[PDB]
View (cartoon, each protein chain N blue to C red):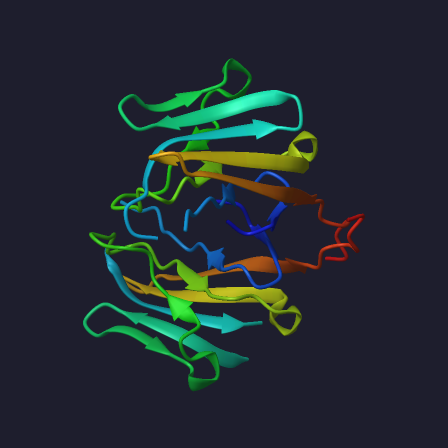
Length: 111
Length: 112
């Protein structure tokens, strides 16, 4: 996993957040670095900010109980910045993974 | 087929080749650079790939359309950027040529 994600404008960007351990995962919250983006619940599955409706997907099943990675669909310029996943872990562990999201605009055509 | 494909440097690029009426069946779909051959989606014989491109070309996850001659080019580099053509041999005599451009984007230096 790389800490910086760069995508072309309008394509979908994966925000990877997978945990190495010895404890299993409870909830993985996703946010921009102050305002909620999504929630991958252990018991309850995926919850998404209405502001991000239809824009948040998980990876295709069968899947990992400890992969908290999400896909942000159809990237725009407004989307770029840094993002934190907060992983509530057992027993008291908290892991926050921050990554930077880069959205690239193509240059003018030659043709 | 989409006429311009844009990708980030180091990424995989989908190179679309969809064939458009009734009784036509697609046989072979060849892929090349303008002059170097890249691959061949053969009806009997399956995917064949140029030596210059080992490990970098896949078909799309199945089930896929017999009239979809699209491939995946793994790991985009600057050299890939350029023009690409797909040629669709169809039953009985139908032929379709799709040309498209590949744009490979380099990220600017970080601010943060």
